[PDB]
Image: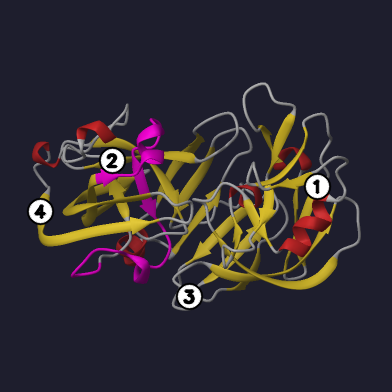
Amino acid sequence: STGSATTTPIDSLDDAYITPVQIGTPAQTLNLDFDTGSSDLWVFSSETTASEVDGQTIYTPSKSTTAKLLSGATWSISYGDGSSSSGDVYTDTVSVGGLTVTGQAVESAKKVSSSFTEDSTIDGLLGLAFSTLNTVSPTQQKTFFDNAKASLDSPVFTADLGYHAPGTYNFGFIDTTAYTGSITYTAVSTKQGFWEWTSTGYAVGSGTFKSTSIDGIADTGTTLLYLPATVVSAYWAQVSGAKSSSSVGGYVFPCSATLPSFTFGVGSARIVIPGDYIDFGPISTGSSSCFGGIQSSAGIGINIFGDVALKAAFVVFNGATTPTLGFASK
């Protein structure tokens, strides 16, 4: 089998992407944030504290003839941005782009933190990291991909995120029309439960490529590109007036600037992030200070190849017995 679903930016900045997901019988379609940096499929629901729901579409398990309470199971998750959610668990039928999994753990939120409430466009998350990170207790549950894998034509999914435009998540096949040139594959460590890999270096604008190993994670659920302070300083040094602002929480730059591109290495291959992808607009409405899309990972404890980086590429998440990651230009 295969599946193919369009993923759509939630706003004009590509802060995140939502993909429609069918849950239950009859189908209830919720727009979920597909997150290769976590491993829980959780939704706003009829069980979510009412004051914490503001415009989201909810899953109502009592209206699904295929929903079953997973007795005794609870979940609780905290994300890198400080947001969190928790609740109980149902199993139900879940379909993405025509690919159906029966018996998928659907984690129903009883509580969500303010940032989730405040974002009316995201109805929950669909985790695509390794199932070892799944938070369901006392019986850990599998991700949608893990459950689907054996049925797929090939044990892969691909992320093709758009810049200020829709893109695609495919399951079970590689669309050879969706990228240019060849796909370069690189090794993955699953030791921390992430799609963790080592970039071979970087360049800033038209500058020379610096060969240096940068360990990080391919994380569709993180907006920005978080890299070592040395790398980030080298980038922003090429933008007149750019500075790190502790009050704002990162590098800012004059909105009048033209940003240079940023290149990262994948083996001997190179992925170029155009400068415009690195512009996240005014820090506050009407400001002429703009927020940068490349930020320091210092104090995160890990480098993160988030959407800023991934959307410059066609990315293969290869879930074969020994997982790997592939990157192509597009």
Q: Give the range drawn in magenta.
A: 111-140
Q: Name the residue under label 2.
A: 22
Q: Name the residue under label 4.
A: 69
- Mark 4 to mark 3: distance in Å? 30 Å
Q: Which of marks 4 and 2 is nearer the N terminus?
A: 2
> Where does residue 24 sit, x and y in percent of width and height?
19, 42
Q: Mark 3 points at which residue?
A: 190
| Whether residue 39 can be seen here | yes
Instruction: Tell me, for residue 197, which label it has, or none.
Output: none
Q: Mark 1 points at which residue?
A: 261
- Mark 1 to mark 3: distance in Å? 30 Å
> Where does residue 123 sit, x and y in percent of width and height?
34, 38
Mark 4: which secondary structure?
strand
Q: Which of 37 and 288 is in front in this view?
A: 288
Q: Earlier in the sequence, mark 4 or mark 3?
A: 4
Position of residue 191 relative to residue 216, above or below, is below
Within 10 Å of disc 2 (Cα), the crowding (few <14, some 14-19, many 20+) is many
Q: Earlier in the sequence, mark 4 or mark 1?
A: 4
In the image, taking residue 168 as reference, residue 248 lies left or right, namely: right
Residue located at (25% from left, 45% from top):
111
